[PDB]
Image (cartoon, coloured by chain):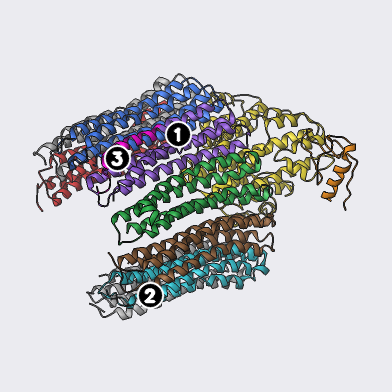
Chain colours: A red, C blue, D purple, E green, F brown, G cyan, I yellow, J orange
Amino acid sequence: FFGAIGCASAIIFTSLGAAYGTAKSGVGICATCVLRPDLLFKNIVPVIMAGIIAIYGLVVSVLVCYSLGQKQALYTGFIQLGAGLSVGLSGLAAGFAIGIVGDAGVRGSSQQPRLFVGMILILIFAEVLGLYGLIVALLLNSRATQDVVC
Amino acid sequence: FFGAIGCASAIIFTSLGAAYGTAKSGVGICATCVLRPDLLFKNIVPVIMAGIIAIYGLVVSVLVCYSLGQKQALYTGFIQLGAGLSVGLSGLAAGFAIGIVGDAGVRGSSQQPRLFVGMILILIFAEVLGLYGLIVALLLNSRATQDVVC
Amino acid sequence: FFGAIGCASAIIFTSLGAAYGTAKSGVGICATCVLRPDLLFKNIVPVIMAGIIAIYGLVVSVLVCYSLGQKQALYTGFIQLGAGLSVGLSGLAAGFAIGIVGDAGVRGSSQQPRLFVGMILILIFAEVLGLYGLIVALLLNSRATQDVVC
Amino acid sequence: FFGAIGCASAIIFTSLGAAYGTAKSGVGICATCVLRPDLLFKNIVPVIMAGIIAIYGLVVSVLVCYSLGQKQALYTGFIQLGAGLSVGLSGLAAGFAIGIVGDAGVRGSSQQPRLFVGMILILIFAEVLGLYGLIVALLLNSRATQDVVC
Amino acid sequence: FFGAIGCASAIIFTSLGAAYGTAKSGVGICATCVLRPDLLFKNIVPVIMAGIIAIYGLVVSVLVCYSLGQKQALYTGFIQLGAGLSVGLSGLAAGFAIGIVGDAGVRGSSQQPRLFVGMILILIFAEVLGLYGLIVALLLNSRATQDVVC
Amino acid sequence: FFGAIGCASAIIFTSLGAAYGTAKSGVGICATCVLRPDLLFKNIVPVIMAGIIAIYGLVVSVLVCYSLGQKQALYTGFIQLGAGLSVGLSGLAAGFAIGIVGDAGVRGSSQQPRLFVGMILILIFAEVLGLYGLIVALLLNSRATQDVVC
Amino acid sequence: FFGAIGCASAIIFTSLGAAYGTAKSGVGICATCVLRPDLLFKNIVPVIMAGIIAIYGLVVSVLVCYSLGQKQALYTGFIQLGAGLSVGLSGLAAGFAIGIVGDAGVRGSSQQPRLFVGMILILIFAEVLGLYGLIVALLLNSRATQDVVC
Amino acid sequence: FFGAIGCASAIIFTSLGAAYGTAKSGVGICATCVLRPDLLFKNIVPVIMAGIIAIYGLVVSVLVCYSLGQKQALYTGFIQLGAGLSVGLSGLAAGFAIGIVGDAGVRGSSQQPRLFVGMILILIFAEVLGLYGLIVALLLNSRATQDVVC
Amino acid sequence: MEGVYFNIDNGFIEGVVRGYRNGLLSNNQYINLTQCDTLEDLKLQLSSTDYGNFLSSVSSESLTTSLIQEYASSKLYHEFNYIRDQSSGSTRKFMDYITYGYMIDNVALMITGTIHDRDKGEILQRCHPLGWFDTLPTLSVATDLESLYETVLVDTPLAPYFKNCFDTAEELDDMNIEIIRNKLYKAYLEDFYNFVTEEIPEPAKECMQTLLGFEADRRSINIALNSLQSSDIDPDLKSDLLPNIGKLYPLATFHLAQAQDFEGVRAALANVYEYRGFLETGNLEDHFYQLEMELCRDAFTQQFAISTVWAWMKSKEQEVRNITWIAECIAQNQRERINNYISVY
Amino acid sequence: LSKCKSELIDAFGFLGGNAFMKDKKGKINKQDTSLHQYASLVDTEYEPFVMYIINL
């Protein structure tokens, strides 16, 4: 219903975000690795960090899907919808952050083979957003299941 | 119905993803071909990666077809529509990523074909975005018919 | 009745895809031909690749036209309409990819005449994008005429 | 009512098409005639190729005129609408291809007058697009038409 | 009603196109004439061409004016409507193609007087669009109130 | 009803048209005049072509006032409306045409005073349009008021 | 109801027009004073010209307001609206014309002080619209005053 | 009611109007002040010129506040709504104009100390719209005030 | 792609540019001009072409070095300065903008030229939007940094030289002639790329776009050759703007520029480029011009595009260089050396 | 001057040569390559009869 578009939102927006993420870092990555091949290992960590946001999205979706009843009310629909939304767009925006930092961090990697850990830290501040949505989304899901109540 | 527009949405969004992937990857490919003429084999495989997204997109669409209602409801329609979106824009996003990373990767191949294999592994990380949506969409289709027309 | 518009949508958007394919490809061919005019034979094989999408689009239209009748049920209309969208716009997107690569490979041809055939191979991958979409519309259509029920 | 919109669509979109086709190709011609004052006959053929779309148009537009009812039916009406669409936007797509290609081909001609047959050849690929729209229309229209008072 | 707006359409759009054609050729003619006083007579000929678009547009308008009324059938209204658009939007596009090639034809005069005739030739083909709308629009006028409006 | 909007419409378009003209030509005139201070009389002949459009509009508009009462038929309304369009579109179109030619025609004056008369010929071709609106509007107006019939 | 919007069109549109005129004019004058510092007094005379249209716009509005009823009549209403439009938009358009010409004319004043008044004559020519608006606006108003009675 | 939407128009648009004026003039005065420090006193007068309008607008808002009561009817509502419109949009436009002349004028100031007043004369011309507006608004406000039908 | 837009302004600007191309020197003419040794004969032959009119205007019984510059400088006034008066819109700002990129290098050379005490009438032909009769003189005589900024503001649209003159104050381009010119060359290319960004969505660029890439690598390679067998500074920008960092790298540009005769990186890079590691300076020069010459010619028949005009503006710079270079050799009764190759390219 | 020169060219030009008299009104001047030349330096077309024109 309004649950199904929640589920869609969750897996879709978190995916758009991660794609961008990967894309940007990827250009930077591909360049630096074929000039120095010991920096292959450093590269790997920005790209996959943006990958895990999507997997929390997938979980939330399964809940809403299963929680859909038989001709649920408009009021019920919105509570389900709202959970789905929270994980998707928080995902999109974490995805944006991780890739923009990631790309400049690939330049950091090349010049500083020792400050590998510092670059990682910048990325990690964008992952709190994903957490912020996921939590709230769960509390909303459990309640969201009412199954007709105007 | 709106169930029919579900099929529509799947096949269109995922075609755009795949198209972008193939387009972009292609430019890179064409360029690289003057700089070295022995990398053709390596160069072509990035393209076929974005080629598997489309196939996933077909199983959903057929699924939806079979599951169509007798005259449907406003709610039935929506469960099916919502599924089309999930596979379709997860595809658009997985397909976009494959093409940027793809493109930059063929400059990678030009300088060093040995760590080409390294770039493939980046490419595979974009495909999971498509998968998570493909999975969610399945479940939705299965729900749509249950409850004897929702 | 919305099926009539189905017929219309398939054959318009798909044609525009081929239009795009040829427009872009043309500019690349016309440029290649003055630099080195012996690549004519190669140059012509890509352009006609975009011409084949449209051809599947007509078949869908004709079949549907006879089954439309003078009047039909509402439910039947809406499935015939959505079916029409699937091929139309996938057609459109397959044409854009074919027109960018088409362009890029003729520029490849001028400078070095060796991996010309690889350029061609990329175009053929976008033709899948039209096919799969086309399959699913056809199935919707045949089943949809029953005067309510697909 | 909806039959009037069929008439217009037909006669408008197909004109526009032809305009684009003729305009662009025209520019290309003018330039070569003062860089090379002997290629007159070769150049002139691309431009005039468009506008023949218009004659197929006149037939379908003229049919819908006579049948433009006082009061129109919905079921009958939309087939009459769709019917116009099909010739028009196909004429547009044909035109758009031909004008891009048209302008670009006079460059082929200017620098070498040996591949003159090959420039034309790019155009012809796009003209089949105008044809397919008409065919489809022909079929919708036949049924849709029931003279005055639908 | 639809008659009133029918009137309006033919006279607006065909006028715009003419305004454009005349204007754009105009810039070119002023430039050429100082650089070449001799070919003044030739230069002038392109601008005068776009004035005649407006005159066919106008013929239709006057005709519709006489059939106008809300005291007559829907059928009179709708026929006025379709007549308006038919010449209106084709005039508009005719205006564009005459004005684009027109501007370019001033250079064609200056470097070769002799193949000035090639310039004219291209223009004479763009004029078919005025004709195509006008034919159809005339007959709609005869239909609305009989024997070309009495 | 619509008849007031007819009046209103006339003053907006025809003002805007004339504005655009006097501006364009003006910049060219003011700029050009530094070179030769004896081009005053010449300079002005562009600018007054457009000064008469607005005043023709004024004759039509005023007529419509007097005829606009506390309440009148729908019939009178739609026909007034249409009288208003006519002057509206001519004012719009003639203004835009003149300002382009004039701007460019000052470069014509400066270098060659002897071919001023050829510049005039251009300017007189744009004045046609003003007339075709004014004529049509008056005719519509006279007819308009006759009252009765929904 | 309609009276308040009557107020709006006149007082917004002529104020923005006048504002633009002043603004542009200003820039030109402020630039010029460094080269030539005694021609200020003559420049200013065009600038203040567009502000007196606005004082008229505001008079038109205040009438319409007091003259509005709560009884409602559409016909009476549209005349109140239709009157404001005329001075609002005529005003906007004068304001654009005098600032454009005005700005270009300060380069004219700069070199050729003596013949400054020739620039004024061209500039002043767009004041007519403001007048045109006033006249028409006044008459409509006078009818419109009735208290929106049917 | 509708009066509260009026009160907003006055306080919002005039504030935006002045804000721009402060902004535009300010950036210019900041540059001027490091190369010429003695012209501080003078520069301060163009920016503060925009300031005087804003105080007009505010006076009106405070008025409107007292004038609402706590409930209003439709007739009363609209007169305050339209009343508010005047100082906000005229003010908005006047504030915009003064910011442009003001800025460009500081560079005039810079090169010729003496003619600071000549720039000031240009600024005051734009103020007439703001004053005039204010007056008109005030008169309407005062009659309006009675509430639940005026 | 392109031509999807309706533009009055572009109509004139394209026709006028095309009008010049048509009178331009052909292959036949170049062959005819090389042959010459008589001063009078050169005059006669040159006269047919578009440049030929200027020769005819004032003639003498002896051709001087002075006369040849004056003809070419006069032709730029017609091709470039005049066209802007008869144009407006976005089309005019593009004519202004590409000229301002030439202006950046040219004025900086003028400013430096003042310090050495070269004259303003001793400045030789180069494209500009105002020739030497206005803006170029006012800039030339002033040696102070402040007064340069004020002169750029009068022009519409504002020229990049405001940013460039601020830089060189703070000593971010250094003191020496070399260093400033190299960094300013990167500035030139930086502004060229930005002008491409604004203009591209309505008219699509193809030949121009490939040409803008090819020019980027090409320029970095010309600075690298120039400062070879001299000195190059590694933290300073003298590696220029490149399209991609995987196409060629900053590192390889800088090694190549340093004095060790390490040509081999150029050769590895070059697989279909006409420049390749060569120690012959002259052979490279022939190759950079031919390469630069191509993708211009395909544009000249491509039309109703902003792309076309760009390629022509850089093509007119190359045509002026070539015409003056052939003309000069015959004046001083020499036969074309490296010049012979670049005539037909 | 022009109309005068034409009446002379037609009257006396026959003495110079049957093909060498063409109609000309106004001084024709050529200077393009060695295929068109007019001057007393070099020429490939000129006046068929001896004529110099003097203008102050």
Q: Crowding near pointer 3: few (<14 within 10 Å), some, many (20+)?
A: many
Identify whether G117 is placed above or below I239. below
* Image marks 3 and 1: residues in contact by CB distance under 8 Å: no
As drawn, F53 above or below D44: below
Query: Are the residues flagged by discs 1 and 2 from a single subunit?
Result: no
Tell me if label 3 and label 2 are in contact, CB under 8 Å: no
The amino acid type of the residue labelled 3 equals Asn
Residue mark closest to the camera, 3 vs 1: 3
Using a 10 Å C-alpha cutoff, classify the residue at mark 1 as few (fewer than 14 neighbours), some (14 to 19) or many (20 or more). many
To which residue does mark 1 refer? C24
Q: Is I190 positioned to the left or the right of F36 in the image?
A: left
Nearer the camera: disc 3 or disc 2: 3
Residue A45 visible to the viewer = no
Question: Could you say where residue I77 lies in the image, as x and y percent from the top left?
Answer: 68, 48
Residue nearest the viewer, comparing A71 with J6: J6
Q: Identify the secondary structure beneath mark 2.
A: helix
Q: Residues within 10 Å of mark 2 (few under 14, many from 20)?
A: many
Q: Which mark is residue D141?
A: 3
Which residue is located at x 46 percent, y 67 percent?
G90
Q: Residue at x 53, y 35 (%)?
A: I207
Magenta highlight on residue F132 = no
Q: Position of residue G143 (x, y in %)?
A: 36, 76
Q: Chain of mark 3?
A: D
Disc 1, SS: helix
Viewer-nearest residue: C121 or E74: E74
Q: For residue E7, which quarter of the picture? A: bottom left
Region rendered in magenta: D128-150
| C-alpha gap between disc 3 and disc 2 | 52 Å
Residue at label 2? G141
Residue I299's x, y, as percent? 56, 36
